[PDB]
Length: 393
Ligand SMILES: [Co+2]
Ligand SMILES: [Co+2]
Image (cartoon, rainbow, N blue to C red):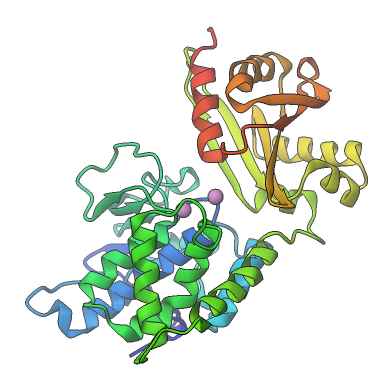
C-alpha cells in the first residue's frame, strides 16, 4: 500500500508507455492558479484512483489506468505558495515527485505522436487555456465554480457549491473506497489544508460537502476513543494558523512573483470580433504595503506594466484583500488602455462600491478601495465580463 509520495515516486519511475494505456495518457489537472485546492484536488483524485484500481472495491468493476496529477505552473513557481510547501512537507512529498507544466510538455513529447492526452479536471470545468494544445479530451470533472456547461458527457461530472473543491473530490472517492481509513490518514493534511484555507477554518463559505469531508477526517484521525476531546480541533486550528500565515507571507518575493502566484487570465468576447485579454492577480497585502516593499509606487507600477506586456494583456487587474482587527478590506487596481478601463470601471463601480484613491482612469492606471468586501475574483470576473459585453464596436 503506497503512500502519496510513494505513489508519485512510482509514477516518476515508470516509462510513459506503462502510464499510458491503448494510446491514451490520462492526467488530472486543477486550474491555472495552482492554489492549495487545485494541488490537493489533483493529487487526491489521482492517488485515490490508484488505490481504488489496486484494491478489492474495484472487483467485477475493472479497467483503470494511472492518472498523472498535474500542477498547472512552472516547477519553479511552486515555492511561491509557502502554504502549499508546508502541507507538502507534512506528507513528505518532494518537489521532484510532482508533475508541472514542464513535465506535461515532456509527456506530450516523449510519448507517441498517435497517443491521446485525456484529462480529468478538478477545481475548474473547462481546460486551462494554457493547456488547450496539450489536452485532447476532457473525460471527467469535479468542480465548484460557475458551470460553463461544457463536456456534458464527462464521467464523473460534479459541478456543485462547495467551500473547497477538495471536499467534493474527497467525498466522491471516500464512497468508492468504502471509507478506507488508511487512504484518509495518507491524504488528510493535503485535504484539510485545502478545506481549511478555503473556508477560513470552517467559518466562511462552508457547504454540506465541506462539513461531511471534515466529519470523515475527524472520525479517522481520532480513532477509537471513548469520548471526543478538544485536541483534534485544537490541532486543526494550529495547522490552520501555519497555513494561513504562510499564504499571507509574500515577503522576499518580486513583484512578478506576486502577480503570477495566484493569477488567472481570460479572453472576454464582446460586440467586437477581437476579445479582451485580461489577467487578474489576487494578492494578500494592501497596495501601500506592496509599494513600500518594492521601491515605491512608481517602481511597483513599472513592474506591473512589464508583467502586463509579457503576458500580452489588454488589461491587468490587481485584487488585494486582507484582515485587520476582525474586518475585511479589499482594493482593486486596473492597468490598461484608458478608453477600455474607464468604461469597464464605470460599469462595475456601483456594484463593487469602488472609491478612487490613486491614479486616474483617463491615464489607464487607477486604484480603488473596494467597499463590497464580499466580492472576490470569482464575482469580479463576471461583473467585468458583463461590463465588457455592453461596450460598443
Ligand atoms: Co482562489
Ligand atoms: Co477551488
